[PDB]
Amino acid sequence: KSKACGRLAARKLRLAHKSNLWASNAYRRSLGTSIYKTPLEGTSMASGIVVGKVAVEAKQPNSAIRKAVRVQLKKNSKVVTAFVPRDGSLRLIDDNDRVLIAGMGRSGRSVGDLPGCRFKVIKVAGFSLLALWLGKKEKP
Amino acid sequence: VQTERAFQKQPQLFLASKQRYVKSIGLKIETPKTAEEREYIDAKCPFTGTVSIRGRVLRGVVVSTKMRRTIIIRRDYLQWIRKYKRFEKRHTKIPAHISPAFLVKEGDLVTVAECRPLSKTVHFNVIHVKPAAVDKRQFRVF
Amino acid sequence: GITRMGDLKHTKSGARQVAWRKKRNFLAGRPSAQTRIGEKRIHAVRVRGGNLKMRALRLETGTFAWASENCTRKTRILNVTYHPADNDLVRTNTLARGSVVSIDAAPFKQWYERQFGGGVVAPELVAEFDQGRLLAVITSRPGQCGRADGYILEGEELAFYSDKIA
Amino acid sequence: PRCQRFHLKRLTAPHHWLLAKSAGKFASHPSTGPHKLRECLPINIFLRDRLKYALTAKEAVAIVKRRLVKVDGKVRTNYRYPTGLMDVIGLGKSNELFRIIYDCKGRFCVHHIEAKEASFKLLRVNQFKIGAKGIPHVVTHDGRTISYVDPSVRVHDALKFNIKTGEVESVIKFKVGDVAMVTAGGNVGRVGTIQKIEKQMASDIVHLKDTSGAVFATRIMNVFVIGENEHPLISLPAREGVRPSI
RNA sequence: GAAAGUGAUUAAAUCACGUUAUCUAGAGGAAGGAGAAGUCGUAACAAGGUAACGGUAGGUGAACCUGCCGUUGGAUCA
RNA sequence: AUACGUUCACUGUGAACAAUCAGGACGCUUAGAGUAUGGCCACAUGAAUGACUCAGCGCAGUAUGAAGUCUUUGUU
RNA sequence: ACUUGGUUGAUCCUGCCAAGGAAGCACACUUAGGUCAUAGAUUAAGCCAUGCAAGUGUUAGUAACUGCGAAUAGCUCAUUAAUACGCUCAGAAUCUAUUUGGCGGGGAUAGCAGCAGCAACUCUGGUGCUAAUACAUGCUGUUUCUCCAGAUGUGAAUUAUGGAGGAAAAGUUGACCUCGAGGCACGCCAUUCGACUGAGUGACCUAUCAGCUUGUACUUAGGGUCUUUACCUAGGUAGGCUAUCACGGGUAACGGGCGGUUACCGUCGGACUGCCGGAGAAGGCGCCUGAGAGA
């Protein structure tokens, strides 16, 4: 009931299945590709030069300014905002350095309070922020 | 009778100072009686001409009777699909040479068996007909 | 070079077929012999597996053969009258297989009196023999074989081709 | 495009030979010969991994080149020479005579034998044809072209072959009620008495029987007609192609 | 028994047209979303103060309004 | 006139067709692995089997499901 | 073979979003020891300094010549949507160095010796000799055509072979090493490693791709090929494929054995995959030598 069940009816079932996959959004997103026209370019981590420092603020109800740097990428020569985690840390980054960017960890989309940006800075100058924030490595 | 520029000739035969060469193809086929009393030559016939039959032996219903001494079969086979536990009807159009010994209408099952390439498309040759009367577009598995 | 390969040409269904590889020396064609008449010469050709296809370029004589009497004499070929494929083979007098060419038959005439004075002969052939140019067919492959020879034209054949000439 | 290639790998080497997966990548490619790649067994491998005389492959190529070994009357200095089914192996110095022959399971074994038996060998007819002056002649599973062979010598008949002189003394005819060791496929290396022969239209089947009383078929080309009615013309191994079954 | 010459054939290369696909500049135009307790109304949820809602036509700053014909998811199972 | 009188699909059975996967043997000190290894007097072995697998090939069985069956008169 | 947080004042639902388990690339922090395996595939099949990877001497061919090898192995996945790969068959339409078994039957150069030329190279010119299992000579078969027969063999060949005729050199003529034995030729048939031609059939998306195809489809004759075929050139018909998805487009597509995930069914990945088969050497294209190359 509600489908072909008969012995010879395997063309109807196989071909109808191919149609119904295009309703599913995960098959649709993979196949369209559709991913290339992205700043990340489908790469988890990207690097390049800092343009400057920007204050972008949270939506609602959370009143807070977040401090995300603007970063030009190496490979595309695009520009994109990118969050800087931990308190301080904007002071540690320095102007016009190379940084390694990675994703917000939400497999796309925009994460917390913070709209727009989908990116966090993992390293600066080949060191890593956690080491820097903790202060068991140095910058000149 | 010999219409075209070249003289059509039964090979492996010398007039000397009619005859006809006829061949038993074997594999359980009766070499039909109308081959032994008919003016046609054809080197691409199994019985009269010089083509040896060998390998795979098919059956299927005739579609076309349009070309000179060539027909088209469709072999008709089920394909099991693993996922859906269920078959589907498939087919395959196999063109095949005919002897003017046979008398073949549209829409009748034949047998064929393969030989050397006679063209691009033709690699098969008719060895036995059953008549049928009276159509095509039935799906028939053998 | 000139290829014997067929992959590039369209399927039965009429589809634009695409290469996956270079041309290859399995499937190498070569130029035609184009085997005319006058002055004997031959060019040897290496092939697959060593060996020699002795390609004949221009041939004067040919080892022709009266079939009905069993007798066969080395005989000088004069011209092509007819060929079933092409009229271009007639114009330049090309010896191919199935090539209807007249012969002097001086040897055959000699054979008849040296044997006899059995024999009997046909009434079409005596109308030919007074001229001394028999019709005959090349049965060899001049290009591959490098040698050209054929039997005399006789019987029901001799009626047929004589209308095609006239 | 592929040409005739030298370097045999292990893994791709056949499952007869009982090779280690380790002990290097490459196996010894057999030279061209009488026998095929798949059925045969070289004499590089024979001295390494049966009799165990030559421990290294350097030592195995030593002793063939000293000219102690003799394949089948002749000396053979070439080594890696394919030797497979019913070949005699005379060995110089501490001389021993072998005949190469299948196990129960399909594997090769090696068998010390009496010298009067080890003169001759058997040879199945694969192909019969006429050539040169109306004379019938026969190719074997070696490739010995036995010309001026007698009548009653058709395909799938064995021929006892005297080795010192190029003779064919007996001829064991194919029939029902005749013992036959199978030499290919799943039933490789099994004795059976031939109960039935089934002609196959076009391209035929033969049904067999152990002394235990199992039953199994095979393709006709696989059977090697070993001797007439129970008692064969050969010393058979331990167990005698019966194969265990619990 | 070499070079040069001529005619065949397989032709790299470059010049040129024509499509074609992916990218990419554009004064303006008209949408869509996001965010600040802006302005102008108050259309909808109660009989929401003219019951609402579908199709269609015209009209007006904006919601909306009116005509013709439907539905009840009505405010009536009478 | 002691074998011949529809073929298939389907079922059973038989042929045909490395490593890995499953699995047997063996204390690599254990394990992942590896194809070994065990007997002080010259011996005994083991390196199985199954799956890989749809199509194509044979014999046997006919419950189900097909085709076979030119009739204002058909077959020898 | 498993659940829990999130729409409400609270409820039961539909419903996704998160959490949660595995691997496979990359970043990070931290680190006694052992065995074992792998490691510039993803992007740039982009570019390359230097060193080295294919050479080859036996008691038995005479530094060279001569003989064989270098077409394998190794690397990579850019082409390729089935022609490749796989799996069944098939050669009665084929070629095959080497092994193996049958059947057979005198003159001219290379190093060496000498005279020179270039900024330069693993280029050579020219003369003065001498080698042979190199090259040429030389005491019934091979190739092809015609005719008469057509096996004791096959499912089947007017096939294998035999006889009677003509032709042709495209040729079998041990002109040979080491001390009675070992070794090396030549030719034909088979055999072996294969190669190469043909058939059936399996599988990634796309209808905002419904009509496509002119050697395109059959036939007769030829050329060419190792053979068969529109492989190519002729004459004669006007055909073939398609809703059982043709044709066209896309691929962040080399195919396969297989790998990861799982209760079963499945599903994703497969450059590598410790193997198999294909293709390519900066990009096309062409060719010699050889059993085998478009190296």
Image (tube, coloured by chain):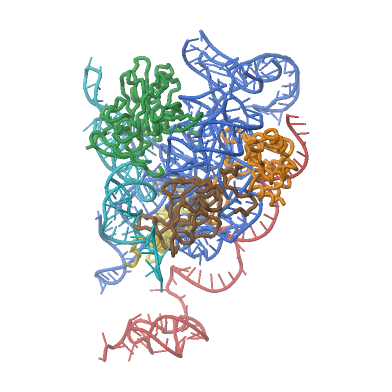
Chain colours: A yellow, B brown, C orange, D green, E red, F cyan, G blue
Answer left or right for G196 relative to G37: right
Answer left or right for G199 relative to G32: right
Of residue G275 and residue E6, the one placed in the foreground of this image is: E6
Is residue A81 in view? Answer: no
Answer left or right for C151 relative to B71: right
Q: Residue at x 29, y 38 (%)?
A: D195
Is residue C1 in view? Answer: yes
> Which x, y percent locates residue F69?
37, 63
Q: Residue furthest front?
A: C117
Q: Quadrant of residue C154?
A: top right
Of residue G58 and residue E55, the one placed in the foreground of this image is: G58
Q: Quadrant of the N terminus of chain C?
A: top right
Q: Residue at x 61, y 53 (%)?
A: B2
> Which x, y percent locates residue C121?
67, 42
> Which x, y percent locates residue G217?
56, 55
> Which x, y percent locates residue F5?
32, 54
How many numbered marks appear? 0
Vertical placement of A66 versus G25: above or below? below
